[PDB]
Image 1 (tube, rainbow over the protein chains, first blue to last red):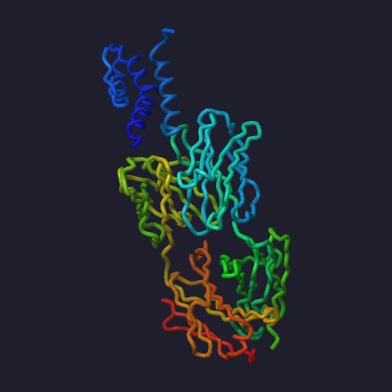
Image 2: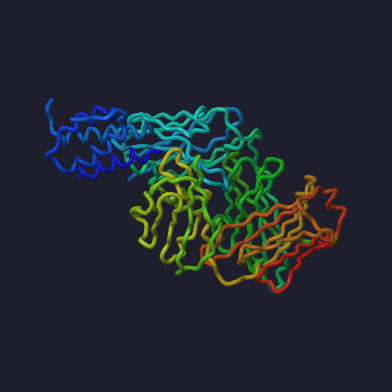
Length: 76
Length: 224
Length: 213
């Protein structure tokens, strides 16, 4: 059941070493190669299909990783 | 180092409430990633998870027991409290508090020493210590077994030592059994050479802390 | 709701041998299973997490494997200190534990020493009688202890308990306690304890006559 949430946390953990609003902000970067997998995993959590401070993506991922870890810990 | 200590052993009468405190050291209860859980183990049975709380107050509970369980944490006191209401005799178990080995995932890496909780209507009672007198005479030629029957006590445990700790070799202190009477019973035995039976003094030291009962029992060859 | 079945319930192996314990889920839980070791009177000890990741402090001879339903803890070459009870744990809520596999040391057959104890004169003054038959320092664990009161075979009115495998010689000791009322005890003469065990080349009876010591 919680396999999908588990795989995404692990991807975000790997590339640095609610679900709809994060994909909408992330599906703007195309010049970066590592985040491709992250974007593919997020669309499975967002029911409707998503198309097309000013801080970096490295900090947005850190924030998202925290929040996904808290969703897991709550079981949500 | 990381250490966890559970509060002293408690006797709980049925339908009443159990309060356990887990005193924590070597880590702060507000540090990112910290989680402390409660796991129980009925005597001679499997482990059962009860509840765990994270540093940010996020709590998970056993689905079958969710309605009876309440877990809380107090960072300054370095404690994690578990409350379990409407206790049943079937809840008689060793209760463990253990730190979680991950900052999101659940497995337990550091564990406390555990604490016995007995749920029962019976009242605390000290044991009767009867002798298991030597099965052979001093001039027999064999090794003779002798011991102490530690009968009818409540609750667990008794500690049995021989000759104030000076006799450790050959000693077999058995697991206690729960009798129909709802009281515990075990035998502690020791094997010695029969040639020593006319010379050596053999005393079994029984200690039943729950009832504040210390007993010294001298076991002697049965004079027929 | 997912169930963790551990197989077998008991395992007999000698030091040096390769050990294989099994844990099986009634539904897929991916690679997320943990393993614990437990010695008597001691807290569990984490060995492996996430299927196969070895815990710090745990010797390399330990390993796990499997994902989905079929999991395994393996021990490449056993050591005396490795014999204990082993539990598996589901990482996922509701964090189910297995029933536990007991790892026992296999050793050369050893017959018990049998001792019979009459009830004490002090106990009889309370109106209860406890006859204790002791089986001492033996292997394997499997033993039959039969009470005979005046050649009448006794069942259900006795209880057994067994010590943990001795740390040095790997033997068990068994106590069997027969319980009778004083009145019932005073009504009979021959109190015998018969023991059948692999190490004994035929059953061995220990007895006493009440009154005659």
